[PDB]
Amino acid sequence: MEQGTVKWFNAEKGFGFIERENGDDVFVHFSAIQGDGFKSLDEGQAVTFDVEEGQRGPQAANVQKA
Image 1 (cartoon, one colour):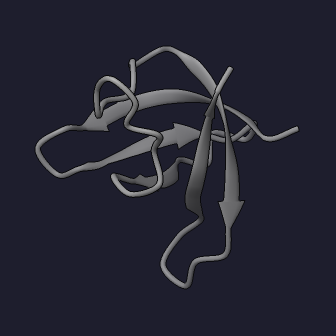
Image 2: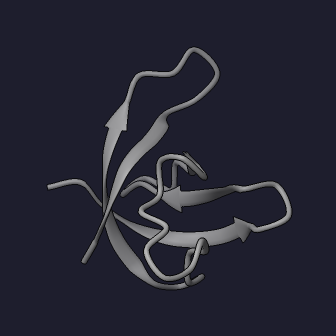
């Protein structure tokens, strides 16, 4: 059950940070978020994501709306 809260969204970058339970900001990508309607993450909103491996950080892929 991979739940996370949107910390802050780098709209001008096309990326964002979603907290893991230990505060570990997971790095989400524009092509990882389901940009249905709008391509942004509501800061403070809780969602789910399919976290993948990443050499330079946890890859927040396949973002599912809670």
